[PDB]
Amino acid sequence: QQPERGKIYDRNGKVLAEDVERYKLVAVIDKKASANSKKPRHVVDKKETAKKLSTVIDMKPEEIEKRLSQKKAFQIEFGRKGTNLTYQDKLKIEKMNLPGISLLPETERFYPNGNFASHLIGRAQKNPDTGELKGALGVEKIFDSYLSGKRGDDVHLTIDSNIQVFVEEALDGMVERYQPKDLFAVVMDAKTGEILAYSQRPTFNPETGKDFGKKWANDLYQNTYEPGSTFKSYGLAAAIQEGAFDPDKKYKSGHRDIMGSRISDWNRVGWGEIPMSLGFTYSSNTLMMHLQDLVGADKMKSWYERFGFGKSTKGMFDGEAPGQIGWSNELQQKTSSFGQSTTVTPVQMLQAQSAFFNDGNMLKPWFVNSVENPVSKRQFYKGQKQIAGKPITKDTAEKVEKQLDLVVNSKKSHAANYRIDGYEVEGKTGTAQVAAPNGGGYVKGPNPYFVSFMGDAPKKNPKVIVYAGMSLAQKNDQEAYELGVSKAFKPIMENTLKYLNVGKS
Amino acid sequence: QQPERGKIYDRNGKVLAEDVERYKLVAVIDKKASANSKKPRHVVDKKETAKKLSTVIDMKPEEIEKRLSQKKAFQIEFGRKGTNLTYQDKLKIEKMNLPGISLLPETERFYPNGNFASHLIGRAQKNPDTGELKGALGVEKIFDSYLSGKRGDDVHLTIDSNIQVFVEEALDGMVERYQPKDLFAVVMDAKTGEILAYSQRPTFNPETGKDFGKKWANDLYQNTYEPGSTFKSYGLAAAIQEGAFDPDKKYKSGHRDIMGSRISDWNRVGWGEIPMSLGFTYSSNTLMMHLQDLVGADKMKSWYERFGFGKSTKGMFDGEAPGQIGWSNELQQKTSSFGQSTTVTPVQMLQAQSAFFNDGNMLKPWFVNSVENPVSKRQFYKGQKQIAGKPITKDTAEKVEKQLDLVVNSKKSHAANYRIDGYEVEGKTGTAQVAAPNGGGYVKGPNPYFVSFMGDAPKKNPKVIVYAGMSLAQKNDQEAYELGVSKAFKPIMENTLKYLNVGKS
Ligand SMILES: *C(=O)[C@@H]([C@@H]1NC(C(=O)O)=C(S[C@@H]2CN[C@H](C(=O)Nc3cccc(C(=O)O)c3)C2)[C@@H]1C)[C@@H](C)O
Ligand SMILES: *C(=O)[C@@H]([C@@H]1NC(C(=O)O)=C(S[C@@H]2CN[C@H](C(=O)Nc3cccc(C(=O)O)c3)C2)[C@@H]1C)[C@@H](C)O
């Protein structure tokens, strides 16, 4: 028999995955089993056996009887409906005292919460010959050789199930309303980098296997996005340190001509000669292009690299994507300033944003708290807060934070739909075009956007960062353009802050 | 967006896997798409569009109309039935000139032979957002970083498609006839170790994904078996080399009393005082136990290790199982002499068996011929024949081969069902009990056996080794006990020798 596979735990000791015993229904149907026996050891009345067994398994009495009639066979099973039976299903069948009926014990992998952080936890699959389980995605795969066994090691995550529930419920709401092609939300402790909650859509159910394999990629570590205007914060931070951003100095908005192409602010005309601070509140593309000119393209590329972009964060997930900084020509450089051409992972965005709230120190995000064996007490691994680098000074960080405050809370804001009543919110919005997966160019349509928000609360001294992103709503794409991910960000952030005992304004 | 993923080829350059273009059906249903256009650019007649589209995709006209009626939606797709469409499917729909209907090109992973060496080749899965493909089993996974791109590298196998066809057809026959729980066949070049064909049952279809994930374990490299009497050849080889086996010296058959358990020959009574050669032809358990006593338990354990058992063969498959030599106490030792308690992988058996046909040198089995890039011409890897060790002398090998010949061809043989008309065959049979995966005994029942044959032909100087094994037939289990895997070995071996131009007599 196999050693017990280790358990996966959340940060408070709740089981996310474990081994349980279930039962498989077996019917001996050959008369030769009762040749030299006092009481029958096979099924005598196929019809009565079918009726009574039908009251415990999800199979019609006609089908049980048909399967019971198979010839040249000593015993039969009943397919998917006959296995994974509970301990109460077992007791019910055995009271029936049906001749030739028995239940075989089987080990299964149990996920108590069903569809729940599924793309992070993953799923283990069973080799029916030996009962051996092997992880095929996420934590179950990454740590397969520790979890596997006389008893395997346990893996404790930084996930908080109470916060995970808020994220799962918000994402179900987004799917219902917007039916987007892709969707993710992540909650990170703003001061440690711990991943407190993470989910995506579409996803699978590790308990049932439903939809497993339809999308291999974990959004947090393996999928890449052109982030859009959330990426302007790192352009802004660079501009501040170089002395190029002055919040009150005016600049020419409108458009710029780059290698013969017209790139303009989102309203085509701009706002004339406006202060640089208002440019960022308005999410002016020409501000960012102007700032790049002042800093210099060469210096700006290094800045984005110093913020950790273009390379893996070296987390503990398999196949972490590196992204890439689009810098080949001046058109790629200029569109990178507002988050197109350059591709990122959500975990890179969390790593970079954390600098604004830790005196300029980027925090390496992390989700594995411990790998340890509960019998021997050996601890193999313990997660830690770690500074991934310090690209900016304390003063630049605070000056970035002042413009993020204004993005949500200026009189001239266009992001008031992210406000939560009783909590002070800040962050940056994004409404990015999405590259055509085959045809080249960008995906066309009425509002073909990846909409996102990189937010934190309470502002200035936040408890958590919440990053949510929604790609290509197929339903209500007008409203997705207007409201972004506000219908996910608000319940996630509000419920998280209350559960973390932060006081309402 | 994505580089072309490299191809998997067979040994003669036939494609086993490649990237193809397929098509996705898209319907624009919003009237606003035809606001400034003379001819309609959206679906005007839902009922006629559905009826006509119902003729190219597998969807009933009511459902096409129901999807076309979705509200707050600009474009709609048709789920799995609307994608993976062929180039002819495209031409047929475009001839209809339906307003608002179009086809998008999509890259798919194409397996030209469908269900074919599936657990060796594996399957790549697509991330719908980016089109990025990732191997999830077998070669597609093991070599994912080479196959992935630019243009990815090709992987050439030693598989011969012509011989693989013989193996797929033979295993289809065994399933229909025997409905076993597990089944495998492998064909290896007797002089190089090249794996010329390999398959198992149950398995999946890499092209459609049907049944993928139901069994993760590759039988050749990852599954373990109590081999049974096929393992006696290595006990025999040790005894020959140690001077303990003399073919004409008689021994007492019947039973031996081992730690209070009576272990007897398969006919319970034995054959009296018979020569050791006849003992082996009969698959005598007491012969192997007597020989083990003569050699010594300590010396015999080392012998099985020099035959490569108990450790991985260090092949190129992921997670190769090591097996284990069952040696805790004398009852484990003595049952190991006839292939119970000890567990092995089929690849270890091919490796050990090859010693008898290469002057005592074990050949390390291998299935990867080349990893190379067709653009740059860089070769990253080239497979080759490799000696895993020389545990026996040339003389011992010859004396083993003489007994394997007799097993099939003695007048007193019980393996005459493995004879092929016109070809001289040799090998060893096995009829082994199977450990219950849960609980602590053997699978009970009328014939609860893993039956197998380790055969080679022509005898003395074989071209290929054919190892087939069938675990726990649920249909015709009496016949499986009597005939073993003969109904698989014979068409596989006969068709292969003919394809290799070996002369029939
Ligand atoms: C960055 O992603 C992108 C530019 N930034 C943003 C952003 O979301 O911050 C946009 S979206 C643009 C600026 N905000 C405007 C807005 O919310 N207007 C609005 C509100 C409600 C209704 C309507 C309507 O009636 O359509 C409009 C719109 C901007 C594209 C970079 C890459 O350009
Ligand atoms: C090894 O696996 C096992 C012993 N070896 C083998 C073997 O397959 O070589 C067996 S099977 C045993 C010997 N061959 C006998 C047989 O085929 N008898 C037979 C043939 C046709 C009809 C009948 C019938 O009328 O029932 C019987 C059976 C043997 C168990 C070790 C582990 O013991």
Image: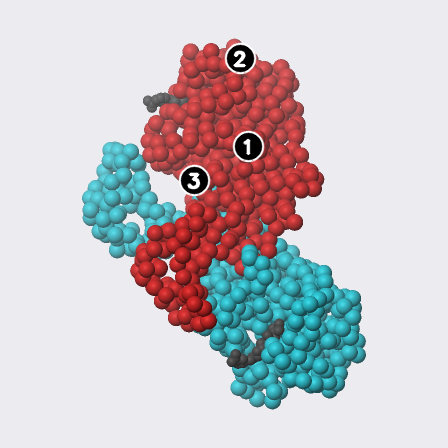
Chain colours: A cyan, B red
Would the CB of label 1 be found within 8 Å of ligand 2?
no
The residue to which callout 2 is attached is B247
Count residues near mark 3 (Cα–Cα under 10 Å), then give few for <14, some for 14-19, many for 20+. some
Quadrant containing ligand 1 reads bottom right
Report helix, strand or loop for mark 3. Answer: loop
Q: Residue at x 50, y 44 (%)?
A: B110
Looking at the image, residue A403 sits to the left or right of residue B23; the answer is right
Say the numbered circle drawn on residue B202: 3
Up/down of A430 relative to A422, above or below: above
Location of mark 1 (residue): B159
For label 1, the SS is loop
Q: Chain of mark 1?
A: B
Q: Quick check: A400 above or below B359?
A: below
**Which residue appears at 30% of the width and 60% of the height?**
B62
Three-letter amino acid code of the residue under disc 3: Pro
Q: Residue furthest front?
A: B38
Q: Are marks 2 and 3 on the same chain?
A: yes
Give x and y (percent) for residue A130. 47, 42
Question: In the image, which is nearer the foreground, mark 2 or mark 3?
Answer: 3
The part of the image, by quadrant, that contains residue A407 is bottom right
Between the residue at mark 2 and the residue at mark 1, the CA separation in whole angstroms equals 39 Å
